[PDB]
Amino acid sequence: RTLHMNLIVAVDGCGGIGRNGGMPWFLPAEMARFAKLTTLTTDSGKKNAVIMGRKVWESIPPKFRPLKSRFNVVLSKKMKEESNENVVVARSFESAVSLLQDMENIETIWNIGGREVYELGLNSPFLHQMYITRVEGDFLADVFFPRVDYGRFIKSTESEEMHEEKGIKYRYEIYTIKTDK
Ligand SMILES: NC(=O)c1ccc[n+]([C@@H]2O[C@H](COP(=O)([O-])OP(=O)(O)OC[C@H]3O[C@@H](n4cnc5c(N)ncnc54)[C@H](OP(=O)(O)O)[C@@H]3O)[C@@H](O)[C@H]2O)c1
Ligand SMILES: N#Cc1ccc(CC(=O)O)c(NC(=O)c2ccc(Cc3c[nH]c4nc(N)[nH]c(=O)c34)cc2)c1
Image 1 (cartoon, protein in one colour):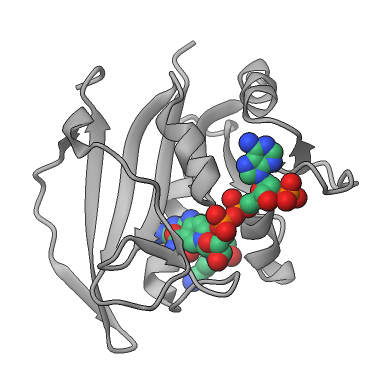
Image 2 (image 1 turned 45 degrees about the vertical axis):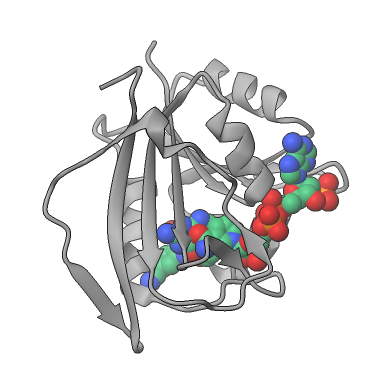
């Protein structure tokens, strides 16, 4: 019945998320946490879904692609269909969300973005939480997280320390839409 769409993203001090079609940094521990958050379900035997844009799909190393143990949905008007049964190509956000809510074995939808995919998520009735990694500094991004009104959310108050790997510092944040908390 209740179906959550959570967003997950890492943004720099300017709100940047991408540079030259890829990520402006590489943070293996942060990536491991990403994989755990998007894969783990409470009901064993249920699966999570990730919804992403074409350029996110093209930015995943083909070894890690499709993202294991998750149902992959790629938004694209130009991409040909994917033979793999863990990947479906959807032509609109509405059709992707309808397809996902039709599937009973899907527990949570993880919106892993592309700016426009994040933007559509922020207007979705299923919007629940934002898991935002805030990375310190300006990585000269050319793609940014959407403009968002944080006044719509409650920022969780659990203790959050600084992290550092590869000389790059970051901190985790969690937001819950006010109409749920
Ligand atoms: N740091 C992070 O957490 C993070 C997260 C996500 C992405 N990134 C980075 O950001 C860049 C990718 O993001 P981006 O915003 O440039 O692109 P994106 O959203 O990943 O991909 C854009 C493409 O997705 C398709 N698309 C988007 N919305 C659609 C819709 N409503 N209906 C149908 N198709 C739709 C279209 O594909 P067609 O052109 O094929 O129609 C569009 O050209 C890369 O640099 C990536 O590494 C970083
Ligand atoms: N170590 C490690 C490790 C282990 C397994 C996997 C695949 C998997 O999760 O199963 C990965 N990642 C990827 O193969 C991968 C690469 C790029 C992205 C873009 C992205 C979207 N939204 C995000 N939000 C956060 N915060 N960061 C991010 O990188 C992204 C997303 C996933 C890394």
